[PDB]
Image: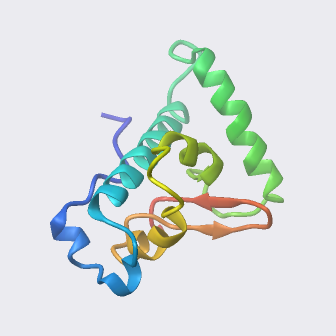
Amino acid sequence: MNDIRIVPQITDEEFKTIPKYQLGRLTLEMMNEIVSKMDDFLMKKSKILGKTNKQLTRSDREVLDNWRELEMKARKRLPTTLFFIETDIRPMLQDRLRPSFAKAIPCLRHIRRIREERCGPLTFYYPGSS
């Protein structure tokens, strides 16, 4: 298949690799929903990069406009092209999940599951590094 996941979910086998020194007030559940939602937005993105006008639907046009908006707002930065903004995943996670992302950043990278690029008033995230 062409459209395949980019980052699976993490269990106690992966979480156990991250001590409280990095988690602090986080938990497997918090990361499970973080890696799940992220993989979703990223999965659909890579799926469009290959799809065509045939599969391209309304949601495909809205995502392309927004995705290209942040990509062009980063000042032609970031060597990658498969990332998203926290403002797109945040409202996709959980309303009760609380602002743990900023704390999970070190927990997600400690395993090499995702990445984070600080570019001005924005924050991108790509699947590890090529």
Q: Nearer the viewer, residue 69 or 96?
A: 96
Q: Nearer the viewer, residue 51 or 6?
A: 6
Q: Is 116 displayed left or right of 40 in the figure?
A: right
Q: The N terminus is located in which quarter?
A: top left
Examine the image and state in which quarter residue 121 appears: bottom right
> Does the image show residue 85?
no
Which residue, as the protein is rendered here, is positioned at the far front?
A: 96
Residue at horizontal 44%, vertical 69%? 104
Image location of residue 51, percent across then percent down: 51, 26
Image location of residue 108, percent across then percent down: 40, 69
Residue at horizontal 16%, vertical 69%? 13
Image location of residue 30, percent across then percent down: 36, 58
Residue at horizontal 73%, vertical 60%? 122
Q: Is 20 displayed left or right of 48 in the figure?
A: left
Q: Is 12 displayed left or right of 103 in the figure?
A: left
> Does the image show residue 21?
yes
Which residue, as the protein is rendered here, is positioned at the far left?
A: 13
How did the renderer colour the structure?
A: rainbow
Q: Is 85 displayed left or right of 99 in the figure?
A: right
Residue at horizontal 57%, vertical 67%? 116
| Count of numbered circles in the view | 0
Q: Is residue 66 above or below residue 112?
A: above
Image location of residue 23, percent across then percent down: 38, 76
